[PDB]
Amino acid sequence: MEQNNIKEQLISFFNQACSTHQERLDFICSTRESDTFSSVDVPLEPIKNIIEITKDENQQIEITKIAVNNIKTLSSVGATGQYMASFFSTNSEPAIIFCVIYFLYHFGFLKDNNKKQIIKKAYETIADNIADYLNEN
């Protein structure tokens, strides 16, 4: 079809898991509002593929910064912004790779040596706060 690779591998799988788009905004919450965090509205079959990606050192690292690459950006979100979600509907490619990050952390998969507030912390601070404007869903 066309160029592709890791990035694609992620999209594919992920895309071959969830359903609609809003799902994401639903995950951030649904995810951190389930019980097993593995019954979410998504198959583990594919997710397992997007899960066995950060099972590598350099990976975990490259991922860490990767996650921050978004956080560092989430520390602005335009000027007249409000919801962080708006900062995804536009670019899915990234909003995807990221979504993967979150989920992982939401399921305690990704690794990152460093105590105190971290990604899962920030990502959660938003995934949650963002769920404060959604509709408690």
Image (spheres, helix red, strand yellow):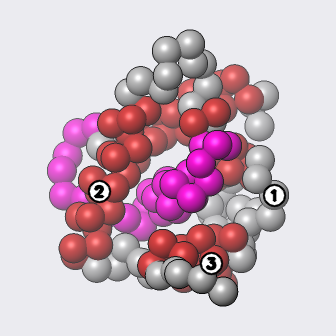
Q: Amino acid at mark 3?
A: Phe
Disc 3 secondary structure class = helix
Residue that lies at the very extreme toward the front in this rendered image:
2
Number of the label disc, if any, that sits on residue 64: 2
Q: Earlier in the sequence, mark 1 or mark 3?
A: 3
| Amino acid, disc 2 | Thr
Residue 92 rendering spot, x and y as whole percentages: 62, 54
Q: What are the residue bounds of the magenta stretch?
A: 88-117
Q: Position of residue 77 (x, y in %)?
A: 48, 26
Disc sitting over residue 92 in the figure: none
Indicate left or right for 128 with 109 as reference.
right
Looking at the rendered structure, which numbered label has been put on residue 13? 3
Cα–Cα gap, marks 1 and 2: 27 Å
3D distance between C-alphas at marks 3 and 2 = 20 Å
Q: Is residue 87 left or right of residue 16?
A: left
Residue 62 place in picture, x, y as percent: 26, 64
Q: Position of residue 50 (x, y in %)?
A: 52, 75
Q: Quadrant of residue 87?
A: top right
Q: Is residue 114 magenta?
A: yes
Q: Residue at x 57, y 18 (%)?
A: 81
Which residue reaches farthest right? 20
Q: Is residue 106 left or right of residue 89?
A: left
Q: Are marks 3 and 2 in contact (CB under 8 Å)?
A: no
Q: Earlier in the sequence, mark 3 or mark 2?
A: 3
Quadrant where the N terminus is found in the figure: bottom right
Check the image and report above or below for 88 versus 97: above
Relative to the observer, which residue lies in front, 72 or 1?
1
**In this view, 98 is above or below 6:** above
The reply to whether residue 99 is visible in this rendering is no
Q: CA distance from mark 1 to mark 3?
A: 14 Å
The local crowd at label 2, few if under 14, some if 14 to 19, many if 20 or more residues have their Cα within 10 Å, is some
Residue identifier under label 1: 20
